[PDB]
Amino acid sequence: QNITEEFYQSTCSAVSKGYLSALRTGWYTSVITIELSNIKENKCNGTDAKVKLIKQELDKYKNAVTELQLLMQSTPATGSGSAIASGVAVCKVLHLEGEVNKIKSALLSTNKAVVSLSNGVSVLTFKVLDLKNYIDKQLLPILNKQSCSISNIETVIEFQQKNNRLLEITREFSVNAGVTTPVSTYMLTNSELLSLINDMPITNDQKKLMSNNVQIVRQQSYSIMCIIKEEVLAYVVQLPLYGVIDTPCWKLHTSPLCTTNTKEGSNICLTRTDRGWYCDNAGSVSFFPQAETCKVQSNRVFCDTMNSRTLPSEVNLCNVDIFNPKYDCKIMTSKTDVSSSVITSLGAIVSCYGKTKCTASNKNRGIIKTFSNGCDYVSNKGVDTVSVGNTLYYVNKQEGKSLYVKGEPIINFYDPLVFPSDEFDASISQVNEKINQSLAFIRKS
Amino acid sequence: QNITEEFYQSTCSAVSKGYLSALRTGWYTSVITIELSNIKENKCNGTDAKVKLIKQELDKYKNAVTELQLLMQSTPATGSGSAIASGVAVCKVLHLEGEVNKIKSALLSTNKAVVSLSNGVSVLTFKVLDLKNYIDKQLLPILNKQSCSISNIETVIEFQQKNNRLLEITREFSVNAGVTTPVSTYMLTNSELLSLINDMPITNDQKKLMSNNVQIVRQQSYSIMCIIKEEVLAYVVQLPLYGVIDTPCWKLHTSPLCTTNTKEGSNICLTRTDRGWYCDNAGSVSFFPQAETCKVQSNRVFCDTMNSRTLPSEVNLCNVDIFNPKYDCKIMTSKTDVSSSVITSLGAIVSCYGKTKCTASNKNRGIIKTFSNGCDYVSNKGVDTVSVGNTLYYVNKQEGKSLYVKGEPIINFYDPLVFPSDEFDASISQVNEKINQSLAFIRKS
Amino acid sequence: QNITEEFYQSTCSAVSKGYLSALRTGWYTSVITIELSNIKENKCNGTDAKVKLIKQELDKYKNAVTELQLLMQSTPATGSGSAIASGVAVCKVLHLEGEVNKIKSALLSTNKAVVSLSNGVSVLTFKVLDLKNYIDKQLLPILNKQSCSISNIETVIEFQQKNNRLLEITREFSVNAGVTTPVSTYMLTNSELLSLINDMPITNDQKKLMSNNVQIVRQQSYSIMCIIKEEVLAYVVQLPLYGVIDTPCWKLHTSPLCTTNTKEGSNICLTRTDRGWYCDNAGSVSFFPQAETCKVQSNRVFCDTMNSRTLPSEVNLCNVDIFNPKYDCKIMTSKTDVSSSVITSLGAIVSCYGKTKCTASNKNRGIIKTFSNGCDYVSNKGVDTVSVGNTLYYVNKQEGKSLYVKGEPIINFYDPLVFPSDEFDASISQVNEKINQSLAFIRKS
């Protein structure tokens, strides 16, 4: 529960420690079934407004079915496609005959049942909506006359409710070529999802975590539609399976670090590279570069290992002894000294250069701190907002202690004349070797 | 109203002048209220189709309420979160007891009223939909029988209209974890928004601008949902507050500038860096790097100062005397001479290199100009489209004069042998210093 | 139908050949019309629930019309705007009087008809919904009384169906400022689209391709709304027109290539630049850098030439003889040896460096291959997934042969001491020239 932060004055970086992990390592596939009604184009001679409204929505029903066949004609266009290979594999098994009828036989008794597929995969099936039973029992004998019948409007409105979810299904499948994420509430109702999470094979502790952070599970799950035949449409919904839980996570925040020399254009800078989410995973650390690829319920981190990067466990040494002999801490160099500010979880790192104003201000008591030229940090305690130049930043109000690690800025240890100031993705060893090789040429002079 | 453009032949860049500003500097928070009905699971013994449709939507009603509580269990996952700290602060004050009842007491008389919160913030409250009064007065005494009643269908359909907006609210909150942008029409009706803009504290001139460009205000506003208790759901909608209006804005367009030497691979190039939106703000210029972070009703520019960058006022000198002694104009160098074209607001900059065709063509009279090797500009007058290689570009038809600033291309002033041709983010001073230091080594030879 | 892949061991790259093209070269504009009803605010003295529901939706009807006028007040804010200049041009012609009435006269007889505009453009018009005829014939004489009438509910529900699509139109136009893509099913029904594709001028073969891959056409089409007047709203829907069909396409996949020296930090790397989609177009090759700018029904590639890049036909030589004297193959250099894996269409390229595990595993028989240090490739035959470190990758199951082109890795031909290892966007000639110039300084020593 304790959330900690440590600002590194020497490297102009901060690490937010005390976070718990939830890394997606596997995929669970579930087949969702809608029992459709195979009807041919009917036409009876009536002008009744009851049967007129039925024709309009039967057309919308028939159009959504025939268009979902047109989408079926479209081969999976998303990807990449590594992330959906499990759902595609289930779709391919549904093509085989004697598999669509297997689902139909197992779902006649109950709205949910486990089925063993031909590929040996044991998946749970769900008949969310039964259009077949309703349309044939309620609406078929009405319009099965020489002229359209005269039934009341109560049955027509209920038919609007049934057809409304199907229209919502085909409209989301069409714009996304049958692969939608996050899984909308119509692909799988929130009530249906919790029932699906309770069934699926994992512990009660792992089920409790997924059922509490539902929205995060929806954003890390794909809805894939596979086929339509035998009066049934089927689409597979992949669900994240998390194999790494409760391992240490920490987020690295980096800000430029320059010198404070007076004459303009005579300053060198460097910035810590590889900022983002770090989490221990199987004796190593998994790096997450892309922003918002990790979701975060407070104190818990949810990420996917597909957008990851494997790093050795010694990578955390760059947060203490950046000159460590074990790992190659990456930095980028430049002479651009623009004033910026990074909002970390328990404060804000501020890099103030030039004449631009840099202040941390509290709305009630006013400005509480004015930042001098350099890189510094302000604790979130008693600080509402932080301003840099003409840009206003707001500080997070998460409760926790923040530590200030004092240290000489490493940018002061380098000579500006032989300093390489255009290294996009370099390391300490490269900067150390490039300078010594540059000084090797000046000695021979 | 006058829109001007100036192409700089020396730097292969153009500036579109004559634009008015609208920079977001603050946030106004408004609490939106939906009076919910606290009902326990009712079950009466009836098969009437009137009461059957009620049960279906009451389940959808109860499910949307209980799921919106599940979303409430999810801590704010978006961000960052600087941009929503004001809305979060209002959400936290709503948690305190004696605050939810304060909103309920002030909204019993009118559908809108200003409320003073515990945090000293004066915010306007809105009861958009009153589900509590309708459900209890119209539907409670019907189903408050030993068996479900037999009321007509007119009341059931009206209940579908009320429940439809709530289902639209929870479905948008669920996919976005309660933070949606742009604010949809269901979070706040267009009619409700104009009424909210008229009330809010600002001048009639600032209210007239927001009420005219509604869609731009929606795209720069966040909908945040805070809590559900005491038969009321509440969600705060932040609205942009613009403190900078009618200050000069101009958009910088840059295109590569190479040499025209015949032998392949013997050409050097450079391109002006920091292209995008520039607007004067409080004695300085605010730079906007990210595209589409600024919206633009013609002749008016709408941007947010959070995605900004503060630059000194002398930054505009890079558009005239790029060799100015005051500011360090940034350029990037390379030897890649690919033919490209940038569509500016009143024409198009064309960089033609190699043998690729570069023509400005009018659909009625045909090709009007053929571009030679180098960087040039064509006015939008009498020009419909511009083609480069196999890529077709269309020119904007905005009315205004365009000026051609003749000048020797600066790429011709540099010696290709000592020229650094791999500078990602460099400046004129660095290129000037790097070449002189390279020539310092050849003199000692 | 044959899909081929060739892995290049010397360059650590693979090319997926055997694909067919479909490049968008032009735009076809179609005017979509909804005949609106011009009604003034009516108020009759009734409390009937039939006429009460009418007032609620007439307000939603009137609000959607008046708000769509507010959106009309917003000048086109999207772009750029090259891609929509054709639709904007049609919108501007609709402003001229005697043009809105021309559409109204030609659509009174049929729901679809071709119209010659003032700009000489021949466009097909579509009256998708006729709100004017329905509202005035069915609902006007009802409420045209001194007190609201007592008509039944069948007509009210049909009015809900008509007004529902209009509310769907204005809600999508509002969030996107009137420019939406992909074109939703409500901007143009799937049934209306196929009828539009059949009419439009092109061959039966080009019509058959568009009608089969409907969803891809929707994602490469824009819906633009132009004006509201004379009881008619109009919005233009641009449709892709493909001028390049059945030309060779191939996708280039690149992975880092490093050395295998034991001592850490003593390795140099290089990676092929310009990975993505390549397609021959008019005697040259069109390069597509941005991912997902090309859609892909299997065996067919759909791209837009606006996000393209024109390259000479000799660019394919970088896939065989990278040291070719005709073209300058671009590579980037670094010393970062991170283990990665690229999922190509018929396998996976794996770059294994360090101690990180690199295995290709089949779920039934287990691990089938362990990758040594370097860059290698594994065929999709009998391989389900491929793991690198803590990241799991899944292989595509597309059927086709894959060829292994053996060759000495070019990274072994370079001396690490004089090797430039920080070239972001460089070429072979630059690396060749930079090393020789570095060796020119060591000879004079």
Image (tube, coloured by chain):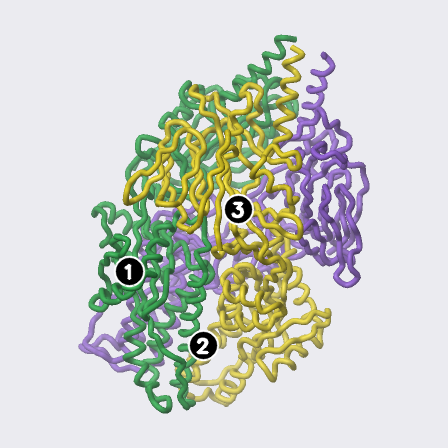
Chain colours: A yellow, B green, C purple
- Callout 3: chain: A
Question: Which one is earlier in the sequence, the residue at label 3 or at label 2?
Answer: 2
> Which residue is the site of mark 2?
A161
- Callout 2: chain: A
Query: On screen, C400 above or below B267?
Result: below
Q: Which quarter of the rendered picture does the N terminus of chain C lie within?
A: bottom right
Is B358 on the left or on the right of C372, as rendered? left
> Which residue is the site of mark 3?
A251
Along the line of sight, which residue is nearer the eye, A274 or B405? A274
Amino acid at circle 3: Lys
Residue sitting at 60 percent across and 53 percent down? C295
Along the line of sight, which residue is nearer the eye, A263 or B126? A263
> Which residue is the site of mark 1?
B191
- Residue A143 position, x and y percent, is 49, 86
Is A347 on the left or on the right of B430, as rendered? left
| Residue A22 placement: quadrant | bottom right
